[PDB]
Every structure is written in structure tokens, then in C-alpha cells.
């Protein structure tokens, strides 16, 4: 419940950032 | 997708690293 | 006491009573008594026939289809104990298909040393539930008393109470009676089997059942251990050897019995260990001169041959003939079609055997938990293989768990092939261990050992899984366990998760809601989530592995230990049973029950009360116009889903630990609005349920409606009178109208109304058309409660 | 249009993929720039795509750090056609930091959709944008949480030039950046576009044009594009494609073929359009892609050619499919949802396999399966494969169900509860008697728990009652009569005539255990039935199988029995309303339990006598207000008893009247000829039998009163009065003999000249004894008489004023 | 007549066959 | 024995007097 | 502790227990 | 390790204190 | 990004590191 | 120091990674 909204994308960027975000190729 | 996993339900760092390359 | 009578060997009686005369002098029977197949007999043929001499039976008593017999009390009035050395299908006393029999009548029967009792298919038999077998049989679990009159009808029972002791069977005391005339004699619990006299004095230590003079071996009716010259003794004194486990005989008797067999057709007795044993065990051979058998200096076992090499074991009496055997020149098939365990007796009878020339087969043995009773089984030669070239056979064993204890046991099978089928609790690990230890690995073909049937209801995963992540929430529990991979990853087909609610810690192994988890795709911990879980409830959870046949390989899956995790608390449910009654004008009693779903340990209750505002229309309505009956009282979520994809202050108080509330400091006969809530958390951001509403109004007083103050009058020139009285500004809620009851002296009395607006606007009431005279006016105020006291009469002159 | 077609794409995580747009002119899809973090403003100042002109679907911008202005990214974007809208939005700019101005000065028209700009704390230049001049629906825009409504950041309009219009009530200049104006075309150039002097372009130009009134110079086409020319419609042989351009058949066919052998939008031609799919009622042909009307329903072919089934979701895509152009291997490790998603399949192009499916008692859900080619054969050349099916009992009702397999052997192994008779029926139905080989079908593993010996049990006697039914069938005895544990009686209501045992493991199949007969036919009597209901009943035997599981049990064919009828239930909700002074409308509801075919309804109505106490109560006093109207344990027990019996036998022997109406085919009735304001009691019954001693329910009671006459409480008749010598008046009036029910009393208001109107009440007893009223001691003058008849309906009409001089 | 005799039915059949002379037993 | 002759197989009237005196 | 602690919950609880003194968390054993 | 005590199994404050500096 | 101060700091550290571990010493 | 660097000053992912094992 704490992670949804802008906090979601911020946290998801924290756990990543160099690997990037997967997308269907 | 991600919203039902993390906001509606409980999600931890495992899901977040799952959503990345 | 002595036994006046002969040894009287056990006999069989058939088709007529001509042979009953042979028991005329029999006080003890050294065998079995089988009276059966009595077709042409009438009840008048048994009244005059009795055998009071008979006391103790060694083997058993068989009664089967004896027509015309109604009770055994006239037959064996002094039958006390049945030893049961040799049973009849693990039963020491059978009453099968007895017609016309009504009651047993063995009032003098006390103990049955070994065996059980089976009474079946007697449609006229009563007085069965009125016997306490516990004091008769040391173990009543193997009794079988069904298909009788008592359990099919409700024939009456006459108990000689007024005497006969009453014993509780499951939860209530019932009378123990053999017949209507005699009832089950009960001895004090202090002397369990030594017996008691009439007055309760305990018999001798060697007495059994009954005795005449207490504490005397010469006055025992039945010998507990051995018998010699009317003296029950602990052991046979020298040089008297033991005989048939009940008496002692000298060397002359054993010698004569042995010699009577040589010149006849047998049981040629020998002597060993101060006993007249028929055949002494393996390793002993008996000489030419004396009857003592000496240990040979070589391996000479006692071989027990088999009729056509095929012996079936289904009962104690079918296995006791194998007692003392070590090598079998035949094949044993074990078939205990039961429902009750017999490993205790089977351990004693069997288990001394080592070799089996033939094959071993287990078929339909329902109660066999394990084959551990083969204590000394080492070799199965299998010379005469079972059809299909099989040496070991196991088929349809509903409870076979372990074949042996391979850690400490040894085995060797020379030839033949194994066979296992429909063993729902014998998993493949034990079968493979046996096929490895025996040495028959390269002997069986396909389908010799069934894989689906063997141990399908069992669980021997023998490998451990660990939960790498446990997380709880309001209604959801998230789990992840470490990956598992057998040698071939294609064998694994998924994980089955079992979870079941369990408030208490103690939970067994192996209800149990099952969830299927697909195998992970090949870090990558499989994991699962549960939803729809009631809060604040402990749960027992474990995970199981699902694999393939594993016939060429030896993969047995894995399982995890049971984990107990409880979901968290939340808002509780609506508080239940709200009632609002007033016991006093200033006190309101409130009763409420805790909510249906506490959803956490309730800490304290929250309640608020406040005064309602009364109806405005109550003040501007005419209360004497007829009909005056006064009532008595998302785009963000869409974008996130699309973009990201997974790779593959009212008065109140805290009521604590209390369900009953009384509220003071309240206006009398005035309603109040009460909302009630339950809270299971107080200090850390107090969490409470939704408000439960209730309203109540206090009961009215007795003086609020009464008008106070004298009566004031004014009169104009035209004899029109305005009358005044101060209203009770603090009434039972409010006053809706006033009644003016004015009378003329010596004339009739008339009444008039004073409404709220009439009094307020007209500065009171004004009466018109009042003749000269002495009037009397009493005023009553009608409030929401009722009628007030009338004012004093208004005496005035106009 | 110098440039490619550039199917829609997205760019993430860096600007390296941004270079893919270098040789592009038009986007035939959606362009997404999102999730950009490791970027700096130095990475965007030297990057531009002037060749880009128009976008078809939409443009999404979301979380691109370092971007300050789009005026350099897209200097020539002009059209957002919005064929597919991202959440009914054609342009979304969400959560951009460092972005200060839009800069899209060339954006002119948006065909459909709306614009959402949100959460841009540093974005300015929004007050100088006239969305009504670009969009066609400005009421759906959502432009909030920006810097304009929170602060007062500078908004430089290059006036000195930029046109100024009104948005709500004030004239504000319209401009895009600090150096560009929001061009506004003359009102005559509604959509053609305007040049430097503001002259209308061709009828097909949209947004901008190089030369006015020339279809060959439009920057964007309003309707369609073809060979550098904008046309209103595609001439033959060109079909409209993607709602914006025209293309011949060759390219569309090439796209279809490329979709045939790939992962897609298999393209078809319909009404000169290459729409993604044929619409309802149509189907493509092999020779031509025409969407010819196969029929309302169509061969619904679904492409996959191997796929496993394990759950509802895996079977969701199969919903509505009729032909599977592949193979099915269903492995359900778990019913109604299975019959929902599946069961419409007629044909499978490959092979069907069932493996270890635990929760499938039968394959009845495959209702419409009729044929399988089996061109692709499972390993072992098997078309139908079955293995380790635990609870599977019946495949299909072969009495009616037709199934044919073109080729392939049969595989049936390790099916514990599948009677071998069904496997035998497989080859006789599918014509595969000699298509298999040895070991193909397991003989010892199939049907190990099935007593499908079914010694035909025939019923001998059936007796039916309205609630109880008694059955009697021919007794059965196996060779060893001790083995018959007892019968099991099954029954369940069957409105249809096609019911066999088909349920999961679950079933209703109300079962009652019957003890074996005492050795008379066994029989059994039933309780608690529903009258006039069809029932399905069959009997099976419970026996103890021998060593080799030889059950040799007996079965009874499913029979259908229909219990008789009885008296029906009470009709529901009888409402009786007076729609007229003499008309009553009666309506009711059908009975809950018809208990047979209802024939008619019985209705009674009786006049209600008014209260006699009203005829004797005085209302002239106070009180004038007028109310206006398990098994294995038992098997082992039996076997234990039998074993003891056998051992004993071996050992012992040694071988040496009211007005009524019959409402038929109706639920309402109308009653006429009833007096005004007359109460009535209505009795209503339902009957399912008319001639032979009607079966009817109990009486249903409802009370009704007719409407009162509006001219029944009016007093009619000349009022005659008598004067005494001492000025005493006797008043008599003729009452309305037929009043509204009854008249409680009369009100008299008399006023002498010069005085006020008095009042007087005449009670019923007073009116009877005085024949009206008797007033005594009258003051001299002239009076008046007015009498009103107050009935239960209310006050009536006053009499004529009787003037008399006293 | 020929039939599968076992249970009480066997006892009744054998008593119909014999019982005027008695059942056999080993002396 | 006897039951394995009569309940398994079929006993003729000749096979029954073998149990008779 | 009343319930199981894992991941972010574990590290947050360890933070609260250790306070200002600080701690080190190395799950890889 | 800490996970083998507090994640897979349960913990208390006393042995949780051992991980502070 | 805006600075997280308090338990959010250790939450961010756990998110960034994960199973690698970290040394959080506010000394 | 961690506290002042990531409380008084904004911190980047790089700063957090330098204090990671």
C-alpha cells in the first residue's frame, strides 16, 4: 500500500537504473 | 500488472527486480 | 481345592446326546469342547441334564447350531475360567448360529486367560450388553458380538438390583447381570485376578476366580499357575515337571504317555527344562534310554513341513502350529482378513523361523502395519516359486508401512522375482531398499513393481525445502522457497502447497487446501501468494514436490517442515446485541456483545452519547382538533500498468474490559443518541470498527407534569374571565396542552382547552360567557409523559 | 514524403535508440519516449528530427530527465491522427522535470482525442495556447498540477505580432515559445490551412500547405494520401489502409503472408479496406482474402500447433473456437468453466491428449467434438492419447455422440476407473477396429475399480403418489450371496429426458442405502418429493470383489418417473382496487407451487355489511374525526465375517352460493355492478382441474371498497319548517336516501340578519326522533337554514337557505 | 439340482442330504 | 476343504454324502 | 518478535531496534 | 546468518540485538 | 531526487543493495 | 557521514552504491 504512485516509480528506479527497464521486443 | 502486485497487494524487492532487465 | 474327576480329553459331540454321558465324571477337560450340529432336539431334552463337575476348559468352547437349547446355566453351572491354550480362530469361546438361545447363564465364569469371545448370528439372544467383559477378558478389543437380538431389537433386561454391582461402560452406570436370577459377580479392585469370597476377603495369591477360604492355596477353585494334589503353586516342585501349562506330573506319567505313542499311530512326549514338552526345540535330540533331549554339536533345526507346500495364515490358531519352527519346507501366504492388529501374538508364534523353502506372499492383510514380526527371517530359497516365477508377493495391503528395519535387519533371496501392487502406504523407497539389500536388482522386469499404486497415500519425500521469504498482511500471505532440481529437470512438474487453518500449535503431518504451483523456468524462487484469508488467524503451511515416475532413477521429491504464520489484525466487526433500556430517570443501562469478527484482541470500547433535538412540528400543531393522539416516546494506474512489463466533542469514555454501561447526569424523560464502536488497538494510531447506532429515552418522573403555583384570575365587566397559572418550564420533555375544567355551583361542569399557541399568544386562557356564581376550576397539563396533578379549585365570583 | 513508414516504437533507458528515427518521416503507429534518467541537457541540444511530420496513433512523454524544450526534438510535427488513443488521449506529457516549454509550434490539428498534461513542476507557456484552434473537443482536456496554477512564471508573448483571441472572457495573445506565435488561420480556412498571407489551401490539405489550392503540395492529407497527392477517397484498385492512406492488393497480401508464418494482425480485405480482421458474419477465402459472408456464425478457426491446458486462463483463448488449427494436450491438475470455454470445438487439425488429469470424471464437456484429422500424430503415431487419468469414468455418450478419427492409433494405459467397454466402443464408433497394434491398449490397468458388469436390474413395480413413490425391482444374487452388501438407490429431478451420471468428484444424485433382502423383492419407498415433477432413478449393487477384483456387480438402466399432481398452492398478492364507483379491478400472482397444469382460477366476492355500531354511535359530541376508508472399512467387515464363516465350515465337516367467476387464461379481472362505497370481501383460489371434482387451494381473502359517488352525500329536497307562537322552528330535510355508505350526522349553520353564522349538530338518533331538528327560542328577525350531509366520504352539499321572518 | 452352496444355505442343503444318519467326524 | 468345493465350484448330490456317516 | 521478519520489514525492524548506534545487515551467509 | 534466524525462523529482541554495531 | 531522511534512508539502502548488504553507521 | 549527506543534501543512486558491500 505504501508503494503506488510516484513513490512506485522512484523505488523501482532505485532497485535498477543501469540494467534498465524490460520491454517486449 | 505492477499496480495489483505492489499497491493493492504486498510486493517486495523481488518483484521490483523482476520488472527490470 | 482339588479336582475330583478325570483329565477327560477334549471331545466332539454330534447329532445326538448319546455322548454327553462321557462327561458325567469330568471335572476338568484337557482340550476343547465342541458341542454342535444338534438338529433334532427339543427344549425338554436339556432341562434334566447338567454337568456341575466341569470347572475349567483348557482350549475353548464351540457351540454351533444346537437346536432346543435356551440357556447354558443348566449345562455348566461351575465353569469358572477358560485358559485358551489353543484357540479357535483367535477366539476362546464362540456361539455361532444358536437358535432358541435366550441368555448365556455362565454366572460363575470369571477369567479367560488367552483369546477372545465371538457371539454372532443368534436372533433370540438377550442379556448381552448387560455383561462387563472388562473384568472377564483382559483385552476386549478383539471381541465380536454382532447380528444378535439385542442390537436388532429392544428385548427387556431384568437386573437383580433389589445388589448387583453397576459399572460404567462409556459414560453411564449400568447393571451387570448374567440372567434375571444371577448377575456378574464383581471382586474388589485391589485383587485383580486372585478372586474374592462372598464377604470381600481376598483369596490366595494362587487362587483364580473363586475360592472358599481366603488366603489358602488348598482352597483355590482354579489354579492360577499350576496344579498338584489340590494345591495351586507358583511352580512345579522337583522332580515334578510342568505339563500343558496347568499341572505338574512325575516322570512316570510323561514316560507312559511317550511309550503309548510308539506302539500306536500322536505327540510322543519328551522332557526338557523340567517340562514334559511334546517336541523340544531346534538343536536338541532325545536319547534312547532317558527322555531328556541334549543339545547336538551341530546345526540341526526343527523343520516343519507343509501340506502340499502351501500354508495360509489367517488366525492365531493357524499360526500357533508353527510355534518353535525354524525352517519351513513350504511356502507361506499371509492373509489376515481382519481390521484389528495381531502382531503381538504373531511375534510370539512366528518370528523364530529362518529359512523358507517356498515363496512368501502377503494378500489382503488389512491390519498388517509392518512385517517386523519375522524376527529371525534370513533366507528365502524360493525353490517352489509362486506362479509367474515370483518369490516375494505383496498385494492389496491397506496398512503395510515398512517391510522390515533395513538399518539393523538382513535378508537374502536366492531366486524368483519380487511383486508389489496396491500398497497404499508402502512407498517406493522401502521396496528399492529391499531389492538392493536382498540382491535382486537385475531380476524384475517392467510392471513387477507398481509405481502408481505403491505408496500413493504415503509420503517419504526424505528431502528438505526451505522457505526463503515469509510475509504476512491483512488478507494475504506471500511465500517463497528455495528452488529444487532433481538430476533431470524434466522430472519436476510443480509444487503443491498445502495450507490449513490451525489455532493450536499441535498439527500432524502428511482440510489441507491444495494449491498447484507451476515449476520455475530456468534465483527464480517459485513462490506463491494466498488471498481471502481471515485476519488474526494462525495458519499451518508446508510445500510438497511433484515429480515423475522415477523408475530408472531414484528421485523421491522433497517437502518442507510445517510453518505456522499468523495474519495481522485489522478493524473489528460491528459490535453485536445492542440494547438501550432505562432503569432510572437519570440512569440508562447499555448492554452490548463483542463483534462477530474481533479481527484482533479487543482492547477497549468507544461510545458517544448526545441529546437529540426534538421535532419542530411538535410545537405548532393544534392538540384539541380531533385526532389529538399524542405519540408516546485510475489513469496513474493505467499508465503504470502499460509502461512497466515483467520479463519472462461529544461526551465519551474508554470502556475497558466491560460490556455493560450505565450513564448518569442525563435529563429525565429525554432521548439520547448513542453510537458504539469496538477497538482492538488503542495507543498506536487507535483502530476501531464502524459506529453502531442506538437511541433511548429515560422514563419520566412523577412531578414534572404537575403544574406548580396558585391560580390567578382576572374578570372584565362582561363577566369574561382570563385565568392564569405559571407553566412548569421544566416538564417531562414538554407540555403540549392544558385542560380547563370549570364548573358552576350546583350546575354541570364544562371543559376547555389551552394549547401551546393559545397560552403563549393570548397571554394565557380567556373564558367567555361566565354567569355570576361560585366557580371551581382545576387545571391539568398534558405533557409527553401523561397527566399531571390538577390544580386547586378556583373559587371566584364574577 | 521523403522517409520510411516507421511502424510505432518506444525508446527507453537512453538516447542510443533515439537515433532509429533519423531516416523517418511519418509514424504509422504510436511514439513513446519514456523512462529516461541518465541524461543531461547537453544530450538534447544537438538532436533533432525535422523529417518527422505526422503521427497516426498518439505521442506519449513520461519521465524524461534533461529535456527542456520539445521545439528542437519535433520542429515539424503537424498532425496527430489518433487512430488508437492511449486512454482516450492523443497527447500525454506526464512527470517531466527540467521541461520548461512545449515548443511544438507546428502542431496544427488533432483528428480525435484529447491532451493531458500533468505533474510538470517546471513547465510554462500554457496560457498562450488555444486548444480550441487545434483540438476538436476541448472539454475532455485535463491540464492541472503544472507551474502556471502554482506560481507566476514568465510568459513572454512576442507581441512586438502574435494573434490574440479570447478563451473565456479576455483577449490574450497566443504563442508557443518566446520566439514563435500560435498561428490562427482565417475562419474561411477551417481545415484547409493558411499560407503566409493567410489564404485557404486545397480542399484536401490539412494543417499547412506550400502552395494554396493544390492537392500536390499539402504537407498533410485530410482524408487519404497517395503518390504525393491528397485524395478524398481511394480510387480502384487501391483499398483504404489504416484510415489514412491507399494501397493496392499486393502489399496487403504480402502483409497477410508475413503474418502467416510469424508470431500479428492477419490482414483481410473487406469493403475495399485491409481491416485487421473480418467482421461478424464473414470469413476469408483461400484464393482471395474477401470477407465473404460464411454465415452469421463462422468457422471460427483459432491458431496456436501444440498447446497444453492446465487452468481456466490457459483455456480462455479457446472460448468460441470451433476449429483448432493445431493440437490439444489437456492436463488439468485440479468443470462448468470447462464447458464454458471449451465444448464448441468441432474439429482438431492434429491430435488430442489427456494426461494425468486428476479432476476429470468424464469428457462430456467436449459436446461438439465430431471429427479429428490427426494429420500430426503424437509420438508412437497416436492420435488419441490417455495416460494416468485418475477419476476418468466415461468418454462420451456413444448412444448419440458421433466421433470419427481420420487416422491414428489409440493409447489407453493406467486408467484405474475407466471401464474397458468404453475402450472397446472407441474402435467401433471411430472405425479403428484394426488400426492399432498389440500393447497399444492396456488390458490389466484400465477399469480396475469398475463394476461395469451391470447385471441388468429390471424394475418390477412402480407406484406413484403426490408426495411418495414406491419402487420394486427384481432381486439380484451373485454366485456367493453373502457378497451382496446392499443396494444403492439414486434419484434426482430430470426435467429433460437426457440424463446420465455426469458430474465432478460435486454431484447431487441423492443416494439412499438399502439393506439386502432377508432370504420378496427388495424395493424401497421414497419420501419428500415435489408433486408434478419428473424424476430419474437407477439402482446399482455394492458387492465385495474377489481376489482378482472380479466384482460381477449388477446395474439398472436409468428410468424416468413423473409423480402425479395435487391441489395447487394459493395465488399470490391479490390486489383489489376501486378504479370506479361501480368497478373493481382484481389482480394477483401465479401460485408458488402449480402442482400440475393450472386450468382456471376461482374468484368469489361478497358484499361487506358496514359496522352496526356506527348506526348507534353519536358523533355530534366530541370525537368528530372520521376515519375514511469409509467404504473399505465396511467391505473388510463383511469379508471378515465371511472368512470366519468359511473357516468354521471347513473345520467342522470332514469328507470321509355467491357470485363467482372462472378466470381462464388470465391473471386479472374486472367487477361491475357494485354500489358506490360498498365494502367487499374477495375470495380467490387456483385450480388445476375443472370437470372431475376440481382440485383447488384454500380461500384467499382481500377486502375492497368501491369508490363513493360524488353526488351521493348531497342533500336533495325542499327543506320545510314550522314556526310556533313563541318563535320555535321545526326543521325537516330529505336525506340522500342512497348516500356514500352512511351519514353519521348533519351540520346546520343558521345566521340571522345582522348576526354571525351559528352552528348546530343533529345526531342520527336526534334526526330519527325529531325528524330533523327542533330549535326553540328564536330571536326576532330573518334567519337562514343550511344543512350538509356528512357521510363517510365527507361533507356533502348544503340545502337551500330557508328564509323566514320572525 | 445343482447350485453354489455356501453359508447357512450350505448347512441347510447338507442337512437335507443327511441327518437321518448323522454327519461324519474323525473318531 | 468343503466350501472351496461348493461355493467356488458346483457340488453334485454325490459329492455331499462324503460328509455323512 | 510476534511475526516473521523478512526483507524490508526485517531491515526496518533492525533499524528501529538498533537505533542511532547503527548496524550492518549482510543476508548472504 | 541473520536470515536463517529471523526470516526462515522466528526471532526475539535479545538475539536481534546481536546485529547492532 | 529529493533526499529521504529517517527510516526511508535505510529503506532506500535496502532497495539499492538488496542481498549484497550494507553498513549503516550513523556515527 | 551518511546522515548529513543524505538528509541535509540530496543523494543520488551513486552515493548509495558507494556505501554498499
Image (cartoon, coloured by chain):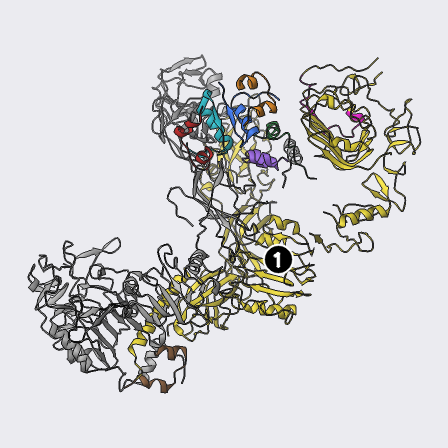
Chain colours: A green, B purple, D yellow, F brown, G cyan, H red, I blue, J orange
Residue G5 shows up from this direction: yes
Q: Please tell me how many numbered marks the rendered image carries.
A: 1
SS at circle 1: loop
* Neighbourhood count class around disc 1 (C-alpha, 10 Å): few under 14, some 14–19, many 20 upward: few
Tell me: D610 left or right of D376.
left
Name which residue lies at 34% across and 78% down: F1
Tell me: D278 left or right of D505.
right
Q: Is residue D421 above or below residue D703?
A: below
Tell me: D561 left or right of D647.
right
| Residue in front for this viewpoint, D474 or D641 | D641
Tell me: D370 left or right of D755.
right
Q: Position of residue D355 (x, y in %)?
A: 57, 57
Q: Quadrant of the N terminus of chain D?
A: top right
Q: Is residue D177 above or below residue D57?
A: above
- Mark 1 — residue? D665
Q: Is residue D158 above or below residue D223?
A: above
Residue range highlighted in magenta: D131-150
Where residue D157 sits, quadrant-wise, is top right
Q: Position of residue F12 (x, y in %)?
A: 39, 85
Residue D693 shows up from this direction: no
Q: Position of residue D672 (x, y in %)?
A: 60, 51
Q: Is residue D630 above or below residue D642?
A: above
Where residue D327 sits, quadrant-wise, is bottom right
The rendered magenta stretch, by its main secondary structure, is classed as loop
Does D132 appear in magenta? yes
Amino acid at each position: 500500500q505504501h508503494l503506488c504512485g510516484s513513490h512506485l516509480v522512484e523505488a523501482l528506479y532505485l532497485v535498477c537504473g543501469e540494467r534498465g527497464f524490460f520491454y517486449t521486443p | 500488472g505492477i499496480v495489483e502486485q505492489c499497491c493493492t497487494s504486498i510486493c517486495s524487492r523481488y518483484q521490483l527486480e523482476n520488472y527490470c532487465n | 481345592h482339588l479336582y475330583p474327576g478325570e483329565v477327560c480329553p477334549g471331545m466332539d459331540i454330534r447329532n445326538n446326546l448319546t455322548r454327553l454321558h462321557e462327561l458325567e465324571n469330568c471335572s476338568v477337560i484337557e482340550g476343547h469342547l465342541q458341542i454342535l450340529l444338534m438338529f433334532k432336539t427339543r427344549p425338554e431334552d436339556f432341562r434334566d441334564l447338567s454337568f456341575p463337575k466341569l470347572i475349567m476348559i483348557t482350549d475353548y468352547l464351540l457351540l454351533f447350531r444346537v437346536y432346543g437349547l435356551e440357556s447354558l446355566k443348566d449345562l455348566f453351572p461351575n465353569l469358572t475360567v477358560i485358559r485358551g491354550s489353543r484357540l479357535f480362530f483367535n477366539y476362546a469361546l464362540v456361539i455361532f448360529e444358536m437358535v432358541h438361545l435366550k441368555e448365556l447363564g455362565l454366572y460363575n465364569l470369571m477369567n479367560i486367560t488367552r483369546g477372545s469371545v465371538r457371539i454372532e448370528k443368534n436372533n433370540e439372544l438377550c442379556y448381552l450388553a448387560t455383561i462387563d467383559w472388562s473384568r472377564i477378558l483382559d483385552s476386549v478389543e478383539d471381541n465380536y458380538i454382532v447380528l444378535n437380538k439385542d442390537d436388532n431389537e429392544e428385548c427387556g433386561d431384568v437386573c437383580p438390583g433389589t445388589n448387583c454391582p453397576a459399572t460404567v461402560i462409556n459414560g453411564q452406570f449400568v447393571e451387570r447381570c448374567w440372567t434375571h436370577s444371577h448377575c456378574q459377580k464383581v471382586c474388589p479392585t485391589i485383587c485383580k485376578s486372585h478372586g474374592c469370597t462372598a464377604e470381600g476377603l481376598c483369596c490366595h495369591k494362587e487362587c483364580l476366580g473363586n475360592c472358599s477360604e481366603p488366603d489358602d492355596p488348598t482352597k483355590c477353585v482354579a489354579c492360577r499357575n499350576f496344579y498338584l494334589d489340590g494345591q495351586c503353586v507358583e511352580t512345579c516342585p522337583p522332580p515334578y515337571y510342568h505339563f500343558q501349562d496347568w499341572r505338574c506330573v512325575n516322570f512316570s506319567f510323561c514316560q507312559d504317555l511317550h511309550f503309548k505313542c510308539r506302539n500306536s499311530r500322536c505327540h510322543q512326549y519328551v522332557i526338557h527344562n523340567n517340562k514334559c514338552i511334546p517336541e523340544c526345540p531346534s538343536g536338541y535330540t532325545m536319547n534312547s534310554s532317558n527322555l531328556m533331549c541334549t543339545p547336538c554339536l551341530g546345526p540341526c533345526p526343527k523343520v516343519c513341513q507343509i501340506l502340499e507346500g502351501e500354508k495360509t495364515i489367517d488366525s492365531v490358531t493357524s499360526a500357533q502350529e508353527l510355534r518353535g519352527c525354524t525352517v519351513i519346507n513350504g511356502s507361506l501366504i499371509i492373509n489376515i482378513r481382519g481390521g484389528n492388529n495381531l502382531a503381538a501374538e504373531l511375534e510370539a508364534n512366528l518370528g523364530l523361523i529362518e529359512e523358507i523353502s517356498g515363496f512368501l506372499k502377503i494378500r489382503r492383510s488389512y491390519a498388517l502395519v509392518s512385517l517386523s514380526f519375522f524376527r529371525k527371517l534370513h533366507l528365502i530359497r524360493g525353490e517352489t516359486l509362486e506362479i509367474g516365477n515370483y518369490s516375494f508377493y505383496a498385494l492389496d495391503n491397506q496398512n503395510l508401512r515398512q517391510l522390515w528395519d533395513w538399518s539393523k535387519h538382513n535378508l537374502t533371496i536366492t531366486q524368483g522375482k519380487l511383486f508389489f501392487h496396491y500398497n497404499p502406504k508402502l512407498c517406493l523407497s522401502e521396496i528399492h531398499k529391499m531389492e538392493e539389500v536382498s540382491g535382486t536388482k537385475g531380476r524384475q522386469e517392467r510392471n513387477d513393481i507398481a509405481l502408481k499404486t505403491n505408496g500413493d497415500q504415503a509420503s517419504c519425500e526424505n528431502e528438505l525445502l526451505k522457505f526463503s521469504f515469509i510475509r504476512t498482511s491483512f488478507d494475504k500471505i506471500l511465500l517463497r522457497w528455495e528452488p529444487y532440481w532433481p538430476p533431470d529437470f524434466r522430472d519436476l512438474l510443480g509444487f503443491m502447497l498445502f495450507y490449513k487453518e490451525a489455532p493450536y500449535q499441535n498439527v500432524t503431518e502428511f482440510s489441507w487446501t491444495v494449491v498447484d504451483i507451476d515449476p520455475p523456468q530456468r534465483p527464480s524462487h517459485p513462490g506463491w501468494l494466498m488471498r481471502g484469508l481471515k485476519p488474526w488467524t494462525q495458519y499451518a503451511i508446508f510445500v510438497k514436490t511433484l515429480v515423475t515416475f522415477s523408475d530408472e532413477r531414484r528421485t523421491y521429491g522433497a517437502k518442507s517442515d510445517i510453518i505456522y504464520v499468523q495474519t495481522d489484525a485489522t478493524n473489528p466487526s460491528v459490535p453485536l446485541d445492542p440494547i438501550s433500556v432505562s432503569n432510572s430517570s437519570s440512569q440508562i443501562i447499555l448492554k452490548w456483545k463483542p463483534p462477530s469478527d474481533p479481527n484482533g484482541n479487543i482492547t477497549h470500547y468507544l461510545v458517544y452519547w448526545e441529546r437529540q433535538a426534538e421535532d419542530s412540528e411538535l410545537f405548532e400543531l393544534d392538540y384539541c382538533l380531533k385526532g389529538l393522539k399524542l405519540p408516546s416516546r485510475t489513469f496513474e494506474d493505467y499508465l503504470h500498468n502499460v509502461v512497466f512489463v515483467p520479463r519472462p466533542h461529544r461526551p465519551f469514555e474508554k470502556v475497558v474490559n466491560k460490556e455493560s454501561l450505565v450513564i448518569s447526569g442525563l435529563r429525565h424523560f429525554t432521548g439520547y443518541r448513542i453510537e458504539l464502536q469496538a477497538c482492538n488497538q488503542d495507543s498506536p494510531d487507535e483502530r476501531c470498527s464502524v459506529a453502531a447506532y442506538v437511541s433511548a429515552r429515560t422514563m419520566p418522573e412523577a412531578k414534572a407534569d404537575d403544574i406548580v403555583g396558585p391560580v390567578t384570575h382576572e374578570i372584565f365587566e362582561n363577566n369574561v374571565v382570563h385565568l392564569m397559572w405559571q407553566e412548569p418550564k421544566e416538564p417531562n420533555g414538554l407540555i403540549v396542552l392544558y385542560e380547563v375544567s370549570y364548573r358552576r355551583y350546583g350546575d354541570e361542569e364544562l371543559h376547555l382547552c389551552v394549547s401551546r399557541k393559545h397560552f403563549a399568544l393570548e397571554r394565557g386562557c380567556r373564558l367567555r360567557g361566565l354567569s355570576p356564581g361560585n366557580y371551581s376550576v382545576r387545571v391539568r397539563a398534558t405533557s409527553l409523559a401523561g397527566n399531571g396533578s390538577w390544580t386547586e379549585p378556583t373559587y371566584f365570583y364574577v
